[PDB]
């Protein structure tokens, strides 16, 4: 019942996490990082688009969960972040996924239990809820957190 | 001879312009506005993606020309502009277009003859070089300007 893709866009790294809702909770399906540090800006964007599509086609999530951007650090970061976010969103929508947006506070409330949880609490609760031994990279962990936020709504 | 697509992205309005490289200069093919005002963001980004792809399938440009963002007006502005910009660029590349980026000053040098031309001179030289009778909407003529910049160069 519902496989969910969470995306954590970034200027240089876009994290992704796929989880499967179970009656018991959520099972880990996949996670990782799409790295876009090198090359022409347009090649970086198209890798994000193509990689998100291929994650979707491989694992069959029907729901995209993303995090509302609140405060970017500056206008340059916001622009690069936005370009990667847009490229990831239209890739999800080309595959026909629904799209839900949650603030950072909603994500932390659903995963940790309080909107002011720090990064360590989030990463630990992501590994607790998904029964992971291996500490995932922070972008993949955030993306998993965002996916879990959408689960069982 | 090349058919060239120029794109002027925007959260609310994305201008497009298509020109054809002739040996005598450049011929007008199409231009207009992609309006994404009302609706959730992801539906707005998907309109941009699908509309840009539709322009490309209709008029057959094989090259994308886009303008570099140097200074966004602010970080709220930059975020929304980057999202539209990423949606438009990955649409172009899914269709297999090459991509060329020029600075605002290169665009004005190629079209008006000098890098500091104002919006008035640019719109008139767009109409002069393409023998247009009607003033295009501003986003359309910027898009045409950006397309003209790539021609022959």
Image: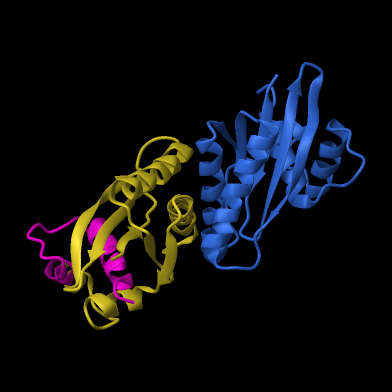
Chain colours: A yellow, B blue
Q: Nearer the viewer, residue B47 or A57?
A: A57
Q: Position of residue A118 (x, y in %)?
A: 23, 74
Q: Nearer the viewer, residue A99 or B82?
A: A99
Q: Position of residue B111 (x, y in %)?
A: 76, 34
On the question of residue A97 being in view, the answer is: yes
- Which residue does the image show at 78% across and 26% down from the upper left? B26
Q: Residue furthest left?
A: A133
Residue A48 found in image quarter: top left
Quick check: A57 left or right of B69? left
- Does the segment drawn in magenta span residue B146? no
Give the prevailing secondary structure in the magenta stretch.
helix
Q: Nearer the viewer, residue B129 or B14?
A: B14
The answer to whether B131 is drawn above or below residue A98 in the figure is: above
Q: Position of residue A130 (x, y in %)?
A: 15, 66
- Which residue does the image show at 24% across and 78% down from the upper left? A117
- Which residue does the image show at 79% across and 42% down from the upper left? B122
Q: How many marks?
A: 0
Quick check: B65 left or right of A24? right
Magenta region: A124-153
Residue B124 found in image quarter: top right
Q: Position of residue B116 (x, y in %)?
A: 73, 42
Residue A141 found in image quarter: bottom left
């Amino acid at each position: 019942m519902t496989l969910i893709l969470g995306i954590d866009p970034g200027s240089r790294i876009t994290g992704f996490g796929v989880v499967r809702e179970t009656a018991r909770g959520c099972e880990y399906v996949a996670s990782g990082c799409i790295r876009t540090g090198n090359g022409p800006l347009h090649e970086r964007l198209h890798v994000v688009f193509r990689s998100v599509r291929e994650v979707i086609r491989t694992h069959g999530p029907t729901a995209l969960s993303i995090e509302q951007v609140f405060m970017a650090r500056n206008a340059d970061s916001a622009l690069k972040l936005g370009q990667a976010r847009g490229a990831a969103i239209v890739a999800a929508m080309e595959e026909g996924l629904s799209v839900a947006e949650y603030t950072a506070s909603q994500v932390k409330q659903a995963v940790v239990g309080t909107g002011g949880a720090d990064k360590q609490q989030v990463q630990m609760m992501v590994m607790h809820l998904l029964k992971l031994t291996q500490k995932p990279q922070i972008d993949a962990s955030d993306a998993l957190a965002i996916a879990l936020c959408h689960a069982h709504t």
